[PDB]
Image: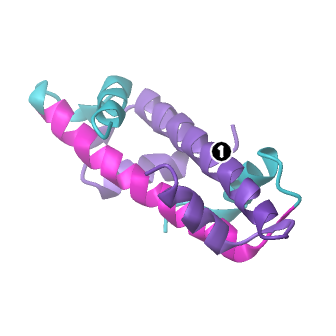
Chain colours: A cyan, B purple
Amino acid sequence: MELPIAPIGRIIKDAGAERVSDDARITLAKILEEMGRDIASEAIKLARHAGRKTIKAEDIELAVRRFK
Amino acid sequence: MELPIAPIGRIIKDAGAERVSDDARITLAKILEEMGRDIASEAIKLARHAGRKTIKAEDIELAVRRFK
């Protein structure tokens, strides 16, 4: 797993939860990482289509729109 | 921002990108954090509906299904 867990617990607390179990932190970290990989994989193909090896903010933005 | 940037660059690299700019890292970190907050905010309401103050893995799982 690339994402660390404590920042994910802080996101849930910032939305208002009073208490958070470890299992909820780990599960939301796993789902964000999965979404992250699917968006990155589409952004890579977009950058390739524009003649680039470098992924830029516009490739990510266009890939998130292409999930609908 | 709660999410740190370096782990987000590692997700994009693990999907195969050869190079990643800082702007792409920052933008994907911002979009995951936004998705995280929307899922956490729905999970809080679900936990409340089940008589709990503690957010559990099942509330997160049901909230991700409820975005469709």
User: Dot 1 surroundings within 10 Å: few (below 14), some, or many (20 or more)?
Assistant: some
Amino acid type of disc 1?
Arg
- Based on the picture, tell me whether residue A27 belongs to the magenta stretch: yes
| Quarter holding residue A52 | top left
Extreme residue in the front direction: B49
Q: Position of residue B43 (x, y in %)?
A: 68, 58
What residue is drawn where x is 49% and y is 49%?
Answer: B67
Q: Which residue is mark 1?
A: B37
In this rendering, would A45 be left or right of B59? left
Is there any visible trace of residue B10 in the rendered image? yes
Is there any visible trace of residue A28 in the rendered image? no
In this rendering, would A6 be left or right of B5? right
Instruction: Using the image, name the chain to which the residue with label 1 belongs.
Output: B
Element at label 1? helix
Q: Camera-side residue: A33 or A64?
A: A64
What residue is drawn where x is 60% and y is 42%?
Answer: B33
Q: Position of residue B21 (x, y in %)?
A: 38, 31
Q: Which residues are magenta?
A: A19-48
In this rendering, would B18 be left or right of B68? left
Q: Position of residue A3 (x, y in %)?
A: 55, 60
Q: Camera-side residue: B8 or B45?
A: B45
What residue is drawn where x is 59% and y is 38%?
Answer: B34
